[PDB]
Image (cartoon, rainbow, N blue to C red; front, side, top):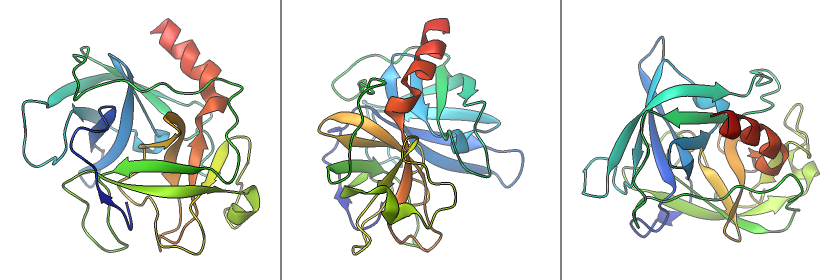
Length: 226
């Protein structure tokens, strides 16, 4: 997260930290959020060999009694997830066991098929990603307030689509989600409307987020099929 501040500890109990093992140059990490006791929502771009989720953390380098680390038993990537258009950058993760609902660890509701959040709104995003273009990731959870932009603010991104994605962050400011923040949710008025997906390598906002309302039925299909 670029140009933000450290979250108050445990003020965002749905924040999930994902450790991912790839079939190549070791682990990478991602943000994501708990939607139900054994299900986390993240980006499809955060798919890997094996994944572990740490729930209830603030500083991911020092464990606390709030910590709950669970194994991912299955990865439901979006099948239309395409590495070219980067469309459908959403994935559901099923946990081997159910997280215990505590004040430090909680669930977040995602929107309905008809909740279409428009340009102008200021939403918040949290994460443990890089704090600058070539800067290390953050040990502590950071968060930044960002403005939703009109579709045109993002047309520099090949294949940007209004119905499926969100254009996030004012072009005139530095604030933005960045590498490492992938998978974390965008909260608008207390509802998760997006998922950090991608942006420029130079970290200049806007960055593109997955628009979740649109995937509601699919999330639903898997959640009901378990």
